Length: 349
Image (cartoon, rainbow, N blue to C red):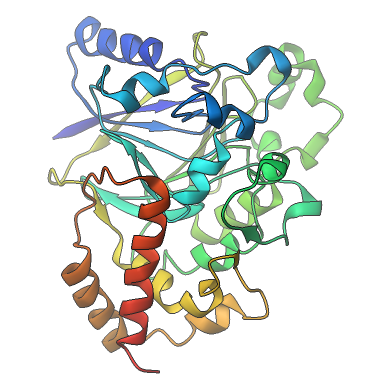
C-alpha cells in the first residue's frame, strides 16, 4: 500500500491550471492521488470586494480561479489542504483562523494546527516572518488597513505546536517561507547560481519561527514555498523540500508514502486539546491572543484525564471528522469558538 500525495508551491489563483496538471499525472503515470497539499498563496477571494485584503504588487490584483470553485461552477477533483502565504485574501483566512473549508475539497489549516489523514499527522504554519509583527495580536473583525500585517507569522504558534510530537511522530509539516538556515543544509552553491539574490542573506534566509518548530518537532518532511524555486535539503531526520510557482515545472512534486489505512480527514486529538486549554488566551474575540497569558503555562495543565474528556466533548459537539460546512466564514468563526468555549467551561478548572 502506497499513497501518492501532491505537494504544491505558490498557487496564486491558478487553480484550474493546477488541477489540469494534477489530472495529467494521474493518467500519464497511472498512479492515483490521495490528496493535495499546498504551501500557501492561495488567493481564496470569494468576490471582488475581497481584493482589498490581497497584498500583491499592482499587476497581480486579480481574482484568480478560486471564485469559480467557491460559486460551485468548478469542483476540486482532489481534497486540497493548504496554509496561508503572503498573497492571500487575509480576511477570509482570519475568519477561519481555526481552520475550515473555504469550498468543497479545499481545507485551510488555520493560523496553525495539526490534522489527521491516511494515518498521517500533518502540521501547518501559515504566513511569512516579519520581526516587527511577530508579537502583534489579531484584531477582529478584519479591517482593510490590516492587509499589510494579517499574513505575518505570529510568535505564539511556537508555543501552540511544540508539544504535538510528544505522543507520536509528525509526518509532514507545512510552512510558506523556509525554515531559517535550511538553505545551508543542501546544495546551496548550485542554488546560488540559479537564484543569485539568495547569496546575501546567507544562513539568515528564512523564518526563525519555522526554524524553531522544525528543530522541536523534527517531522519526516518539511515542505515550503514562497521562494519560487526548487530546493532539497536534509536537517537531521527531516527532509526539507521547497516548491515553485504554478505555471513552471517547479510547482508540483509528489510524495509516495506508506499507507497503513485509508482514513477521512480528521482533527488531531493533541491539537484539539491544545486548542481547548488555550481558550482563556483567545476569549476576547476582538483581540487574540491575549499574551498576558502564557500559552505554555495554559498547556502545562493538560492531563490524560482532561485530554480524554476534551476529545469526548469535541466528538459530541463537533465530531472527530472534519466535514464540509457551507455557512459563511464569519458565522463559522463564531461557531467554532462557541464550542471551544463550551468544551473548556465544561471542564471546570
